[PDB]
């Protein structure tokens, strides 16, 4: 026997993802605005078919490892790693796309900044960040791959570009590729998404001569002993149960189950 | 004395090409450059070729 409802576990409410998957929560999908508020939880709930993730098409590098790392996370503290108005004075940060609607309009992710030319020139880009928050910091970025050479020339003024991300445990260089691709969600270009964890006392360095979707917000994670991810369809209500399944909650002391 | 270089290691089970990358890195043990290390296991009767 089970209740048939998701509910509390040791006095802490779960984090209901709703219509968002993990990509839409960590990237800042425009339909997932309510999930970006400093908070804490006991476990994570997923709708089985959630269709609000990467609205711009591309490949999320190491999705399932990010899921395994975010399984044992108690709380996050969302902070602004790079201020948008201050840190980019020589580029235009106002970049929107029609592949991500918001309120019958066009908008972008809430944790990333699309950088484009300003006054006909794209200067060299080099930024650094030092972790001092005494905990791990999750950093996300992306690399743009356009459809033709005219798009690349109109948005970045160079045929060849590169992105370099260096930390004390991360060291990787990216080059854009231009080809003809099938249309997904009305766009033929791609944006490939990447992530890393900064340790305390470590420094991350970004360099770019083009094709960078720069970070805007970052997460400060805290670990915990008991948590997990549950895929479920039962509605959320109130209890104080010590046991939780996808099909409901359990309140007894018998040694076995078949739920 | 070259802006561009390459290393090639070829065997009957190994075939890899390496291109050096130049960037600004945080200092570990007082040095900013890096050296990346690699290994292989030659079988009996096999030949390994280094080009650089
Ligand atoms: C088989 O495949 C290969 C590879 O896919 C094909 O090779 C490609 O061919 C095309 C066409 O021949 C080449 O494009 C040309 O590049 C020339 C060099 O560019 C220089 O000048 C640029 C100036 O930038 C300004 O103009 C561009 C438009 O060209 C604007 O987008 C931009 O915003 C600026 O306003 C520099 O940016 C650049 O760095 C170089 O210094 C161009 O001279 C040439 O322009 C002609 O065509 C334009 C229309 O596209 C026209 O508006 C111009 O007036 C001019 O007539 C053109 O863009 C590719 O460079 C080449 N690829 C590579 C890797 O070399 C190959 O053609 C294909 N085979 C067949 C048979 O199709
Ligand atoms: C969030 O998800 C909804 C549906 O899960 C998306 O709405 C769909 O958008 C596509 C366009 O790509 C339409 O073809 C469908 O008809 C829409 N379905 C519904 C039910 O409206 C919505 O676009 C997603 N939003 C983002 C930002 O990804
Ligand atoms: C979420 O928490 C962060 C701290 O982790 C808050 O950021 C701080 O905000 C206060 C007030 O503006 C500043 O004085 C601190 O300097 C900020 N700290 C950092 C490291 O950015 C953030 O405001 C919180 N957001 C909420 C309340 O949702």
Image (cartoon, coloured by chain):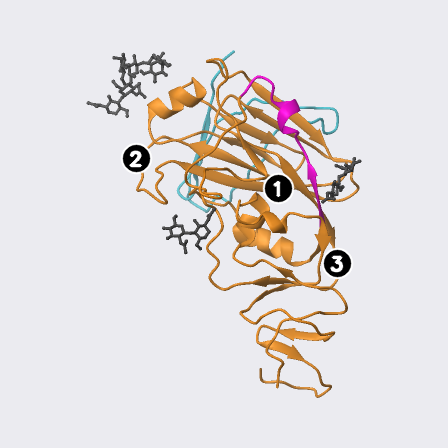
The disc label shown at residue A235, or none: none
Q: Are marks 3 and 1 in contact (CB under 8 Å)?
A: no
> Alpha carbon of mark 3 to alpha carbon of mark 2: how far?
46 Å
Residue tagged by mark 3? A224
Of tags 2 and 1, which is closer to the observer? 2
A133 lies above or below A67:
above
Percent x, y of residue B25: 65, 26
Question: Are dots 3 and 1 on a single chain?
Answer: yes
Mark 2: give few (<14), some (14-19) or many (20+) Cα within 10 Å.
few
Q: Earlier in the sequence, mark 3 or mark 2?
A: 2
Q: Are marks 3 and 2 in contact (CB under 8 Å)?
A: no
Q: Which quadrant would residue A220 be assigned to in this image?
A: top right
A69 lies above or below A181:
below
State the orange chain: A
Q: Which quadrant would residue A93 be assigned to in this image?
A: top right
| Extent of the magenta region | A75-91
Please, which chain is the residue tagged with disc 2 on?
A
Query: For the point 62% across and 69% down, which residue is it?
Result: A236
For the residue pair A162 and A96, the one nearer the viewer reads as: A96
Which quadrant holds the N terminus of chain A? bottom right
Which quadrant holds the C terminus of chain A? bottom right
Please, which chain is the residue tagged with disc 1 on?
A
Q: Which quadrant would residue A3 be assigned to in this image?
A: bottom right
What is the count of numbered marks?
A: 3
Residue tagged by mark 1? A196
State the cyan chain: B
């Amino acid at each position: 026997s089970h209740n048939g409802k998701l509910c509390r576990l040791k006095g802490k409410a779960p984090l209901q993802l709703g219509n968002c998957n993990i990509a839409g929560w960590v990237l800042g999908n425009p339909e997932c605005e309510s999930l970006l508020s400093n908070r804490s939880w006991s476990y994570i709930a997923e709708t089985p078919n959630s269709e609000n993730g990467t609205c711009f098409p591309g490949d999320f590098a190491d999705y399932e490892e990010l899921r395994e790392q975010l399984s044992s996370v108690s709380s996050f503290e969302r902070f602004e790693i790079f201020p948008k108005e201050r840190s980019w004075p020589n580029h235009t940060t106002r970049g929107v796309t029609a592949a991500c609607p918001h309120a019958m309009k066009s908008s972008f992710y809430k944790n990333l900044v699309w950088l484009t030319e300003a006054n006909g020139s794209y200067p060299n880009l080099s930024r650094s960040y030092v972790n001092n928050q005494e905990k791990e910091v999750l950093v996300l970025w992306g690399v743009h791959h356009p459809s033709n050479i005219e798009d690349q020339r109109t948005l970045y003024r160079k045929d060849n570009a590169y992105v370099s991300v260096v930390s004390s445990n991360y060291n990787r260089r990216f080059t854009p590729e231009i080809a003809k691709r099938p249309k997904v969600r009305g766009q033929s270009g791609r944006i490939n998404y990447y992530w890393t964890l900064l340790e305390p006392g470590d420094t991350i360095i970004f360099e770019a001569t083009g094709n960078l979707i720069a970070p805007w917000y970052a997460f400060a994670l805290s670990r915990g002993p008991g948590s997990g991810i549950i895929t479920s369809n039962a509605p959320l209500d109130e209890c104080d149960t010590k046991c939780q399944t996808p099909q409901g909650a359990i309140n007894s002391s018998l040694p076995f189950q078949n739920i």
